[PDB]
Image (cartoon, rainbow over all chains, first blue to last red; front, side, top):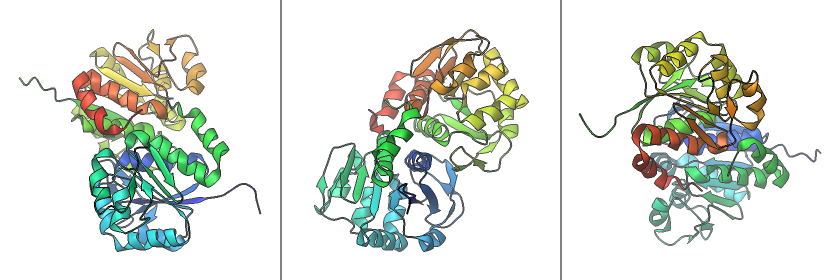
Length: 191
Length: 191
């Protein structure tokens, strides 16, 4: 078929998610032509984020989970967002399936602690927000990195709001290649 | 009264606004303790942004306009967002009042072309997204800058999604001072 990759992303949006860490990847991936489904963890109703920005999901996770599999599953950070994701059986199942099928998992900031909660990617080199380091490293199930973006095979992690553009472009690069990522980067006026 | 500034921001959210350029300033200003009202240009219902992210306003502009004045009026970019803002009599009135009372106006990316439409801040040094330069400069009503953030008195402009953190921190600095801006910057993991 076509040499032009048509890819799909699942972004899981929980109450208390960091809104910048949600919107930057969604926007940047859509700029790349990735079909992104913003899926509300609890359901389809609008989601109150960490600084009270309210984002309306495209669908409930309930419904979006049925339209899998996805080329990447994306978890934003935010302490409460990460907590909610960590407590979710539905999220456990999706991550496990994604890992089982050798699909990309991309998580940022406090997000990676959801990987810890769900026993996903043990033994990976991972980064997190500096403040989430101890939580992530409790039990020594990973090797820690200070890299702004870290990609260890199909486990892609990043550090904070300030690494969100780099994180999103790394996802684009992994799904669609370097040239597509360069195209999307070009008008962003990034440093 | 208190030596600790309690400040208020009005962010005007139009259909087709750039969602990153909306959420980054809202989040960053709220991190600073600024009371931010995300006001929907057309009303209080959820607003579809440039890459289809849907953000629920705190209020209609109709209602928020009555709770003025604000310490800063913020206009995000996005071509369609900027167009809608440029066509709005309500926005014209708010900007004029803000300029008349020597209050801050902060605009990013395509956003500054709304200043042009409304004849706001003529003779200011301003920047825009590179692609919006010609539109902004039509009629020679401003002096152009390539600075990532440009502040000419009470007219603060910036270039794109990639300058959004710098733009938001500049607003924080203008309202609450350098130390508050440093506090907010510290955990962002910015380059």
